Structure formats: C-alpha cells, structure tokens
Image (cartoon, rainbow, N blue to C red):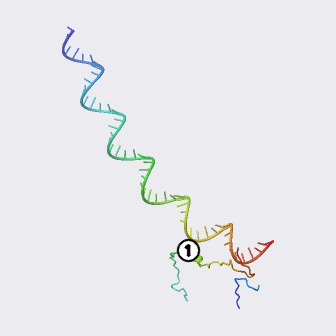
Amino acid sequence: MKRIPRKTKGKSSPATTEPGTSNREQYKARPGIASVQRATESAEMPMKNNDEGTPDKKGNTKGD
RNA sequence: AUAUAUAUAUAUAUAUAUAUAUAUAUAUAUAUAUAUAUAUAUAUAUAUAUAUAUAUAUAU
C-alpha cells in the first residue's frame, strides 16, 4: 500500500571504468539553457480562472 | 682779404653691431582627429537581501 496526498480540500474532512564516461564539458549553449528555461516557465502557466458571474453553492452569483 | 694742409659738425657710399617685421630649422602650450587604458551612466545574465502578490502554516 502507498499513500498519495491530495492537493485539494475534499468534501469529507574488474575495471568498471568505461572508456567513454569521462566528462569534458567545453560547450555553452546558444541560447543558454538557463535563459530559455525561464522564458518557457512563463508561457507554461495555464490562464487564470474567471469565476465572476457564475453562481456559488449557496446559489448567489459572485462578483461586484 | 685769398689759396693749400689739418680738426669738429651735417649729408652720401662701404664694412661691423643691435632692435622691429618676414622666411627656414628646433622646442613648448591650447585645439581637432585616431588608438589604448581607467572611471561613470545605461542595457543583459547569475547570486544575496528587502517589499508586494498567490499557495501553505500560525495569530486576531
């Protein structure tokens, strides 16, 4: 058995040295990885919800 | 009173020296241009701190 936590509030509550593994990192990306990752993080986000106008569980529409 | 010779002064010519203007060479200062270096400001990236917003927790 394993447990997964909820993100919402619910209703009820030998020479093994291989001859190729040596690291020689001489390469810098163009564009750099760090820069592009930051940019993708922003477009990655889903667009915001628009609750206004809709009713609530009580029955009254929310908004101003 | 006259002539020749001699001395001083004025004028002219030749030689030597000085000052001003002009020309050539050398040096310095200012300006412009180029190059290098430094500093400052602006922009980009990384790290730290502060503030604000969202999520979570605590308090009212």
**Amino acid of disc 1:** Ser
B34 to B49, vertically: above or below: above
Q: Secondary structure at mark 1?
A: helix
Residue at position x 55%, y 74% in the image: A35
* Pick the front one: B5 or A29: A29
Q: Position of residue B7 (x, y in %)?
A: 27, 19
* Pick the front one: A59 or A29: A59
B38 to A17, vertically: above or below: above
Residue B16 horizontal side relative to residue A10, left or right:
left
Q: How many marks?
A: 1
**Circle 1 chain:** A
Q: Position of residue A13 (x, y in %)?
A: 77, 84
Q: Position of residue A16 (x, y in %)?
A: 55, 87
Residue A4 horizontal side relative to residue A33, left or right:
right
Q: Using a 10 Å C-alpha cutoff, classify the residue at mark 1 as few (fewer than 14 neighbours), some (14 to 19) or many (20 or more).
A: few
B2 to B27, vertically: above or below: above
Q: Quadrant of residue B53?
A: bottom right
Position of the C terminus of chain A, as image quadrant, is bottom right
Q: Position of residue B27 (x, y in %)?
A: 40, 47
Position of the N terminus of chain A, as image quadrant, is bottom right
Q: Which residue is mark 1?
A: A35
* Pick the front one: B10 or B16: B10
Q: Quadrant of residue A60?
A: bottom right
